[PDB]
Image (cartoon, rainbow over all chains, first blue to last red; front, side):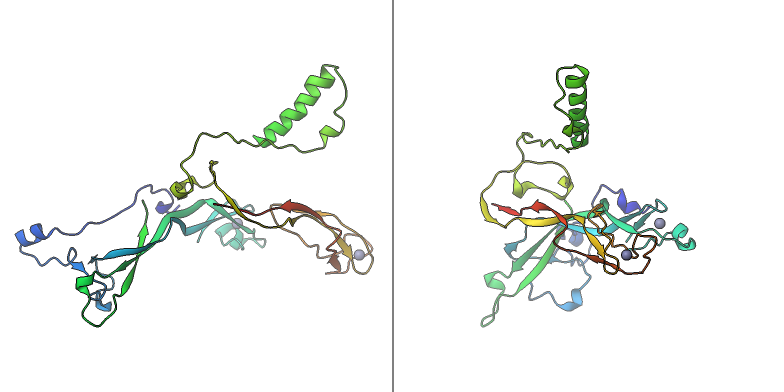
Amino acid sequence: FPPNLTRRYFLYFKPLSQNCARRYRKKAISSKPLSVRQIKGDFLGQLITVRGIITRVSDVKPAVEVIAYTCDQCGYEVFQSECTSEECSQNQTKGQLFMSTRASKFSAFQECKIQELSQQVPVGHIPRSLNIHVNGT
Amino acid sequence: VISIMDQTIKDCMVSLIVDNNLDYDLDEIETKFYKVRPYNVGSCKGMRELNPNDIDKLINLKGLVLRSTPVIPDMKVAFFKCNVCDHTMAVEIDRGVIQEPARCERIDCNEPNSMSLIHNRCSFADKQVIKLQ
Ligand SMILES: [Zn+2]
Ligand SMILES: [Zn+2]
């Protein structure tokens, strides 16, 4: 069975400290505080730090990742209507899939909107906002 | 626990009344279904503190009622009648699913897809949706 069904831990990363990067003579980008206007599409997939003010906080919501099904015909557990397991696939009769929330993988989810600070906005524009997803503990 | 309590009540009627020969006012109790509802769980952490790991675990809350829906009838037993020979079945619900017969159950009448659902001869159960703040 997939390892993620039993992992009780969550992984997080914190960025390089500017003092350490300067000490080791490297140009750290991860810890640089960025406004949503400076956040272009080129930085998609990069590890960045966003500086701003929180405007909206979504409440805690469950978030499914792998839906677990059970088949009474063969007893196998299928992880994502009709059972696709090896026994049912070879057999002429296939069992019906029933969802099992207990074995399904769930995570705590919230969404928050960040907005630019006043000094970050050039004259004549409107303070844009960006969406932040928070997962795990 | 509820199934245990139902069996316990059945045992209580059998053991404490008729086995004790006190009386026999239990004939219908063998058939009726019971349920025991726990209420005084220790004080809980409130709605805003709940977490995904708390799913399926009994908790306690307080709040205020805002909106109440009317008594929605939920299906428990389905009533089917054959559209060519007028035979009547009684199909119960197993885990929230309705199994529609594909053929009439009578030996003489075997027409496929000959069964029809009669809405108003079914048996329903009361469902009420309440909103709490
Ligand atoms: Zn199967
Ligand atoms: Zn018939």
